[PDB]
Amino acid sequence: EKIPIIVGDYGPMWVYPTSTFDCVVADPRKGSKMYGLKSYIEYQLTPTNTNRSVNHRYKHFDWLYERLLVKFGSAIPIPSLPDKQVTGRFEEEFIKMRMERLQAWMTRMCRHPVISESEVFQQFLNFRDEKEWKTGKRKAERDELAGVMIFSTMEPEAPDLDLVEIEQKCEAVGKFTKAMDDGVKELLTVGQEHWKRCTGPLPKEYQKIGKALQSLATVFSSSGYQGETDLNDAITEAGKTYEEIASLVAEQPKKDLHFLMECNHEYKGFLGCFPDIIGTHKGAIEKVKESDKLVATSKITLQDKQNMVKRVSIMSYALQAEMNHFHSNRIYDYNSVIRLYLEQQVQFYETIAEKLRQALSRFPVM
Amino acid sequence: EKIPIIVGDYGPMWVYPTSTFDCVVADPRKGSKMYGLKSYIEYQLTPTNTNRSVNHRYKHFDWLYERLLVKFGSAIPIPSLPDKQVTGRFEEEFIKMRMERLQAWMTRMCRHPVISESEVFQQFLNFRDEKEWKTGKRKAERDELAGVMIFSTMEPEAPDLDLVEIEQKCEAVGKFTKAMDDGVKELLTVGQEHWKRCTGPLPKEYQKIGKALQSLATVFSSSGYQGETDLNDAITEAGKTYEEIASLVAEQPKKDLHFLMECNHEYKGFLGCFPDIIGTHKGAIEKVKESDKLVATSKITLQDKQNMVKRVSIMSYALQAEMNHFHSNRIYDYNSVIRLYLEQQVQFYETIAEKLRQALSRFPVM
């Protein structure tokens, strides 16, 4: 099973294929298994590498998830699959957001140099027989090259680093991830906090204003003063213009804030995984310090000792390999969502301004 | 003393001069009257009609106020002079807002067809000797043509109106003013409410955001990942950009909301003069209903009766005359402040947008 690690300017990294490939997930189908009124939803996965489509119910993705988690979980963070919700198994909204989350989940895997070209993931996609599948699902479940053993399939195209060099790279990752986790948890709180404020009390204000104005115009109109008519219209419109800004405001987070939040959630997810991934490397590095203590107590041999080293190094490269894939994608992701949030923001203010500028051009120069 | 009332399409109205004139008030001077460390502030009133300047301490305006109130108070609402404040007699802020309120107060009087061309108001302005003034202040205080008597100087260039027609115009004014008063009191509340929200909790938010972002960039920068540098700068700047929006926001009401509020206060003031002002007329109209009852009880004569009528009509024309001056100016005033508030609003949103659009363009492109 080929899992190579090469070095570079940025340091170790996986070998990214030259012939990249993604995958689409849509067309919420409906399929069946004698139970009466209990038909599970089925999605369609259309790879790009070969155009040959396939179907999969949510339960199969969960299955896929556990496999990937069990197989590489000790080295590669595995994207979280969405929760198992409010018993709303059948309408527009539900399938939509779920299919949205599955789409993003699939693309993550497809983009991963190591996962995307594994047997389990691959066979998960390209399969014809309704039984050619059962065979794979079976082969998958008996693959003992999982857990820590996955490192046994990795081949570093570089020298050894002592136990020392290993422990150090471990600490580093552990300090970055904890830091970024703490950092994203805030960005998430203020955002959720700002969100809650733009969809609630803020609109009501512009709503109270716009109404306050309109009632006043109504009062002037009862004045019964010769020589007026033009103003009460300008006023009344200003109010209605404000009411629309109330709507525009209360309906904006769904166009920008939302994406910024989602991106952060996805990442809070990757981060939540390091607590585990880091405890295993720590134990591994700690177990390699006893090498000397062991060799002297005549428990193992120098060859056994030297293996423990060349072996725990592979671990680092894999956790070096994984981070390098992380950072790579982190930098791309935040640069796109922020770029997106701002753009939407801009248009937002620009739009409001134009709305005011209109009600304005209704009041004479005097 | 000429105080004529003519009729028109809109009905009775004062005779507005053809050669209009305003007056400026600025340059907070400092005068002295041997008390030691007790020098009262003095303002400078520069009429436009003749360019000859004059000085006046606040105490003199109060004096002017009482005179105008005593003289025409039974027919013309007299703008309120600002309160007598927090014992902060000497700095930037205080004199500024006070001088602002005096300026607007003077312009109100200058714009009034009846007040502007009265002896007391006029002499208040154009006077040379430090004694030529004492003479006027003296002449003013002995003018018995005040209170109800002011109507004796009014000349209606129109026929007589009957008690019925009178009571009706009275009710009307009473219903409009009460209505508009109630209406402006709200516009004032939401505004004060919106104000308090833009100078407090709202900025703190954009402040928390901008900081949340900046801490996060700080965390990424500790990552120690080969292949990044450009993003943490874009992020950190976005935060600082938000902090500036916090300032911009918390500092906006002073540029628009403020004028809109002030205009409403001034008017809440005219309205508060309600009452008094339409229950001398109310009493007058009520006293004219007893005309018949009297003439029959042989208390007065038909000639006496017919006088009461032609006489209470003059009152209406003078009042009616007052409203027509009110509405006239009301329509101009609201059309200018609203026009002003919007314009400022527009620029506000336009500015914020431009600020975002900048942090946006810090975007790479990768």
Image (cartoon, coloured by chain):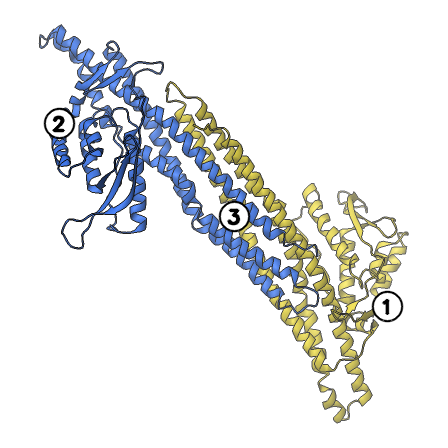
Chain colours: A yellow, B blue
Residue sitting nearer the eye, A207 or A6: A6
* Label 1: which secondary element: loop
* Residue A113 position in % (x across, y down): 80, 62
Determine the CA span between mark 3 and mark 1.
Answer: 51 Å
Residue at 61% from the left image edge and 49% from the top image edge: A342
| Circle 1 residue | A2
Q: Chain of mark 3?
A: A
Q: Amino acid at mark 1?
A: Lys
Instruction: Tell which tag, 2 or 3, sits nearer the viewer.
Output: 2
Q: Chain of mark 1?
A: A
* Residue B93 position in % (x across, y down): 32, 49
Residue A49 vs A150, above or below: the answer is above
Q: Are marks 3 and 1 in contact (CB under 8 Å)?
A: no
| Circle 3 residue | A197
Q: Quadrant of residue A224?
A: top left
Q: Are marks 1 and 2 in contact (CB under 8 Å)?
A: no
Q: Are marks 2 and 3 in contact (CB under 8 Å)?
A: no
Relative side of A209 to B303, left or right: right
Residue B121 vs B359, above or below: the answer is above
Residue sitting nearer the eye, B248 or A78: B248
Q: Amino acid at mark 3?
A: Arg
Count neighbours of disc 1 (C-alpha within 10 A) and say few if under 14, some if 14 to 19, many if 20 or more. few
Q: Chain of mark 2?
A: B
Relative side of B332 to A312, left or right: left
| Circle 2 residue | B143
Q: Which mark is residue B52?
A: none
* Label 3: which secondary element: helix
Q: Amino acid at mark 2?
A: Asp
Residue at 76% from the left image edge and 78% from the top image edge: A312
Residue sitting nearer the eye, B75 or A209: B75
Residue at 42% from the left image edge and 41% from the top image edge: B257
Instruction: Tell which tag, 1 or 2, sits nearer the viewer.
Output: 2
